[PDB]
Amino acid sequence: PIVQNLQGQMVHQAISPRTLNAWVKVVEEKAFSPEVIPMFSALSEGATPQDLNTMLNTVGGHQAAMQMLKETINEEAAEWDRLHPVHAGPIAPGQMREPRGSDIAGTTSTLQEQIGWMTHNPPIPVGEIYKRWIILGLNKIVRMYSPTSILDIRQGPKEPFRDYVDRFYKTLRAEQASQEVKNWMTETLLVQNANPDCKTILKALGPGATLEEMMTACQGV
Amino acid sequence: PIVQNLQGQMVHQAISPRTLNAWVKVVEEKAFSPEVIPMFSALSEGATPQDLNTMLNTVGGHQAAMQMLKETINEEAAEWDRLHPVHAGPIAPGQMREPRGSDIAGTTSTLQEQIGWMTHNPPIPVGEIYKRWIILGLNKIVRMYSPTSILDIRQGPKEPFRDYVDRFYKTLRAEQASQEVKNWMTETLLVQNANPDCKTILKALGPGATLEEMMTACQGV
Amino acid sequence: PIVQNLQGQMVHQAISPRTLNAWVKVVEEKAFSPEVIPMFSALSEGATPQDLNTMLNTVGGHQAAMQMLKETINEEAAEWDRLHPVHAGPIAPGQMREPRGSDIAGTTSTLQEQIGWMTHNPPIPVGEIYKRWIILGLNKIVRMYSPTSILDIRQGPKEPFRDYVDRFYKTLRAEQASQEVKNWMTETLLVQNANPDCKTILKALGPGATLEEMMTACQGV
Amino acid sequence: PIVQNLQGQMVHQAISPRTLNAWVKVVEEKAFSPEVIPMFSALSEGATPQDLNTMLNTVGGHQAAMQMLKETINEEAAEWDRLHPVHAGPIAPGQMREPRGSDIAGTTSTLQEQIGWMTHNPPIPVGEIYKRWIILGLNKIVRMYSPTSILDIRQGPKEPFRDYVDRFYKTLRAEQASQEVKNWMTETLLVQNANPDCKTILKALGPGATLEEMMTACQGV
Amino acid sequence: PIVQNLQGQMVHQAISPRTLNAWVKVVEEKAFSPEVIPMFSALSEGATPQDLNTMLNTVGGHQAAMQMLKETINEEAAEWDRLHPVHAGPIAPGQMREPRGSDIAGTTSTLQEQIGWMTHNPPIPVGEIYKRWIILGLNKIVRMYSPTSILDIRQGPKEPFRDYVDRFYKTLRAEQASQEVKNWMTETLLVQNANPDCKTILKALGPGATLEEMMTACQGV
Amino acid sequence: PIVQNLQGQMVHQAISPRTLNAWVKVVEEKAFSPEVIPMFSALSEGATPQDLNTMLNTVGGHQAAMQMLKETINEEAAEWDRLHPVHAGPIAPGQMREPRGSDIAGTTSTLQEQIGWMTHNPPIPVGEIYKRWIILGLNKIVRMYSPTSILDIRQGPKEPFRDYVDRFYKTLRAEQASQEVKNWMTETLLVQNANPDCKTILKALGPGATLEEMMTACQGV
C-alpha cells in the first residue's frame, strides 16, 4: 500500500503477512457472505491495484465466482476505456500519461507508475475506481450466490416469530432494492408470511407499530 | 480513528485487523451480554462515524437486533435534526458547515469532513453523540433480549443461597432503574424469594446486615 | 493509562486489546485465586481510575463478589471523604480542586481532571489510593471465597507428606495473619496434623529442623 | 531483505521468524497449489538471493520437486552465463564486478556484494532474475504435479453444473496456454462435457451467453 | 525492568504481558526441570528486585518449593547483612544509602531507590545478587525434586544402549559435582550398568573410545 | 544479539521470547532433521556466544546428542588454541586481548568483552567460528542420527516410482559427499534399485534423460 511516512510524505510499504492471512481466513470462513464487502473495504485501505490483483490471485477455491469477477473487472475496464477516450496529440515531457482500464486493473501499469498517479498533484483515485468494480462484481456474486428468494421466507407453525424476523432481515440484508421498496416489503411481506396465531396478534397491534412492540407482542405464541 | 502523532498533531490512522477481529469475536462470544458496552466503549476510543458504521456493517447474525439498532440510530438522528435547527443564512467562506443527524451517522459526511469537525478549534464531538445513540440503542436491545424478569428470580429448596445471590446481582445487573429503587430491591426481594430454611436464618440477622455476613450466615443451609 | 512519551512528558495512551483480553482471561481461569492480585497490580501499572472502572465493569460472572467489591469501593470512598474534609473557602483560580472519594473512584472526575492531578507538580496518587481499596476488597473476597479452614488441613493415612506440605503452604498462602503467628502455625500445626507414621519420624528430627530435611525425612512413609 | 530506513537509505534487515514460519506453513498446507506463487511473490518482496536460498533450503519434504527446482535453477543460471558473456579485460578499481549465474543464485556472491549490486546506481535486479527462475521452475512443478487433464473434466449425470464449472476453472487455472486458446476451451469444452439434461438447456441459450445466465439456466437440472 | 532509551539514558519500562505469561507457561509446563534456570535468566535480563518478587509472587502451585525458596532468599539475605556490616557514622547528604539484604530482596527499597543504585555511577548489581540467590535456591529445589539417584540408572536387558545413554546424561545433567568427578562417572558408571551383551561389546572397544563409536558399537544389541 | 541502532552504531539488544520459543519449538518438532541447520543459522543472525550457550543450555531432551555436541565444541575449541598460539610478550594498554577457544565458546569471556571484539575495528567473527563448530557438530549428529543407508533405499514391487524418488533425494539430502559422487549416485543407484517393471521402462528412455521425463515415464507402472 501507499502510506504516509513520519517525515510527512506518501511512500509505498508492503502489506503485512497476518493482514494477508486475515484476508485468506475471511474468505475461508464467510465465503460469499455480505460481511466480506466492508471487511474487504477496511483491509483495502490505501491499497494499490497491484495489491488488489495479489489479493484476487491468492484466492483458492470458488473458481466459478473468481472467473465471473475477472470477467466483470474486464467489462468495467472496457467501459472505462469507452467512457474516457485517449487524449489529444502526443504525451507532454512535463507530464505523465493518462491511465486506461488495464492501468486501473494494474495490468499495464508498473508500481512506480501507480505511485506517480496517486501521489502526484492532483491525484487520481485508480484504487477507488477498481474498488467500485470489485464491490459491483461482489454484488453480482452475492446476488447469484443467494439460494433463496425473499417471497420464500415464511414463519413455521411452531417457529417463534423472533427466529423468523431474524431470517427476514438477513434475506432483506441480501436484497439490494431502493429503501422505499424495502419499507414496502417490511410492512407487507413480514406480516403476510407470519403464522395464523401470531398473524392474528399482529392484526390487533394496528398500524404504526414498531419492532420491539411486535417482537414482545408475539412472544407467547 | 483520529489519533495524536509524535509531531503533536491529530492525524487519522486506520484501525487494526486484530482490533477488528477482537470486535468480531466479542460479538460472537457474548452476543447481547452487558459487557459488550464497556468493551465497545474501549474499542471505540478515538473512533470516527465512518469507523462506527464499519463496525456495525461488519456484523453477521442477530439481524433483528441490527435492524432495531438502525432504526434507533435514525430516530436519534431525526431527533438531532429536530433539536438543532439549521442556522441563519448562507455558509461563511471562512467557516465550515454545521453537522446534521446524517453527518453524525457518517452518511452525508466525508472523512475529511469528519476530521475537520473533530480537529478544528472548538472541536465538536460527533463520535460521542453517535456513541450515546449506540449505547442507548444497546440498552434497548439488552432490555429486550433479557429473557427473565427480576420477580422471577427465586431460591431453590436445595439451591445454595450463594448461587442465588449471584443470579440476583446478574439480573439486577440487567435492570437499569434509579439506585434508590435498586436499594429497595436489594433489601426486599432477595430475602422474600429466599428459601424457608435460609429465610428463617436471615430473619435472625436483623436489619443493618451486609453481604459477607448474609453469605456466611446461610452457608450450611 | 498515563505513560511517558519519547519527548519526556507524561501523556495519556489507551490500553491495549490483548492487555484487555489478558485481564479477561486471568479472571476466567483463576477466578478468586491470590495470583490474581500481583497480576492485577502489574496490569494496573500507570492506570487511571477510569481504566480501573473499565476493567471492573467489563467483568462477566461472579456477581455476588462484584457487588461486594462495589460496596467496599463506596465504603473506602465514604471513608476518604470522612478523613479528608473539604478545604477552607472558595477554590483559587490559579489552582485545581482537591479530589473527593468519588473523584478517586473516577465517578465525579473527568479524564482530563484525572491527568491534571497525576501530571501536575506535586502529583497526587489517586490510582494508588483506589488500588489499595481494590486490593483490600480483594482480600475480603479471597478470605470469603476460601472454602476450607487451616485447622481442617490434615495428612491422610496413605498420603505422602510432600502432598500435604503443599496443601499447607497453599492454605497458609490464603491466611493473612502476622508473620510471628504464621511461624507459630508452621512449627505447630504441620506436625500435629501429620500422620502417626511420619509424625513418629518428625519427632526424631528434634527441633531446629528445616523443610528439605523434613521433606527428605518422611519420604519412605 | 534490503529495505529502506527512516534516514532515507537502503539498508539490510533480517527476515522475521513469523514471516519464516508463514513460509513454512504455506508449504505445509497448500504443497504445489498455484496460490503458492503469488504468496511466494509477496513474501519475497525486497528479498536477497541469500534469503531465497534460505527459504528453499529450509523446506522439508517434496524432495523430488526440490531436486527438480534445483536443477532448473542451475539450468537457468547456465543460461545466464551463456547469454551474458564475461566482459572485456580486467575489472576497474573504480567499479564492481558483473554477476554470473552463480552470483544470482547467491552461491558465489557474499551479502555485501548482493547489497552492492542492488543499492548501487544503476542497480541490477538479481532478485528479480532469480525470481523468474523460481516462478518458471514453479510452473514446471505445478504442471507436473497436476494429476488430471482438462479433457478428463466432465459433468456427472446427477452432478450440478455449478460444481462442474468450479472444477473447470480450477483445472483451467492450472493450464498455462494463450488467452485465445483458453477462450476456445471455454466456449467449447465446457458445454461438450456437460450432461445431456443441461446440455439440452445450454443449447437453448444460443451463443453470446454469459456465466451468470448459464449458471442460473442449469440450476434445476 | 530498567532499559536503555533511544536518547541514551537508562529508564524504567514495565515488563510485557506475553513476557509475564511466557514466565507463567514455563512454570506450568516444565515445573522444576533444569531448563527453567537459563529460561529464567534470559527473561530476567535487566530486571528489578521488584520485578523478581512479582514473578515469584505470581506463581500458583508448588507451594512447598515456593516456601523453601523464600526461606533460602531470607537466608541468603541474612548472610548479606552479616558479611556486609552497616557503614561508619551518618549517611552523607551528597550520597545515597548502602543496601541491606531486604533492599536486595526489594522489600525495604522503593523502585526509585532500586533505579538510583543501578543507574548511578558506580552502579551496584543488586539484581545479580538476588539472581544468584534465586539460582542457588533453584539448585536446592532441582536437587531435592530429582526422584532418582545416578547409581540407580541401569540398562535393561532389551533396552537399547542409546535410550540408556540419554537417561544417563539427563541424570548427569541433574548432578552438580566437579567436572573431574563427572568425568570419572562417565568412564565408570555408564559401562558398569550397561547390559551383559553390550557390556561385552564395550569391553572390546578398549579405552580411549568416544561416544559416536560407543553408540554405533552397541547398535545391533 | 548485537544489532545496529537507529543512530548508526552497533549496540547489544536482548533476544525476543517468541524467538526463544520458536527455537524451542523447532527442536521439539523436527529433532535432528537437516532443516534445523538453516533454521538455526537464520535465528543465529547477529547472535553472541553467550546467546548461543543460552540456546544450547535451554534444550530439553536428546541428551546423548547434547553431550556429543559439547564434546565437539570443546574439541573444536582445543583445536582453536592449538592452531592459534598465544602472542608475544605482555598485552598492550592500548589494545585488547586476543581470544582463546573458551572465549569463543563464551565461557572465559564477558559480554562486554564479546561486544569489544565484534564492534571494534578490525572486528573478529567469534560468532561465525562458533557457528561452524555448531554446524560441524550438527553434521556429526545428523549423520549419526540417520537410521538408514542410501544402499538400503529400494523401490517396492507396487510402490510408485514417484514415492521412491522422494525417498531417494531425502536420503541423498542426508548424504554429505562431493557433488561428482552424488551425480554418480543419481545416475546409478536410483535405476538399479528401481522395480523390474519401471526398470524396464527406464532402460527405454536411454541416457541423457531428466527427472520430469523419468517421472512421467514410469507413471502407469
Image (tube, coloured by chain):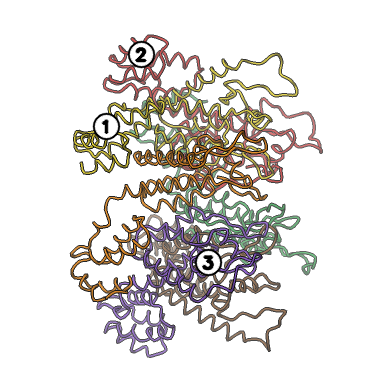
Chain colours: A purple, B brown, C green, D orange, E red, F yellow
3 and 2 marks on the same chain = no
Quadrant the N terminus of chain D occupies: top right
Judge depth for marks 3 and 2 and give the one in front: 3
SS class of the residue under badge 1? helix
Which residue is label 2 attached to? E192
| Mark drawn on residue A127 | 3
| Furthest residue in direction front, as rendered | D88
Give the chain of mark 2.
E
Up/down of A201 relative to A110, above or below = below
| SS of the residue under disc 2 | helix
For mark 3, name the chain.
A
Q: Position of residue F85 (x, y in %)?
A: 61, 15
Residue located at (65% from left, 72% from top): B116
Q: Which image quadrant for residue E201?
A: top left
Q: Quadrant of the C terminus of chain D?
A: bottom left
| As drawn, E155 above or below E122 | above
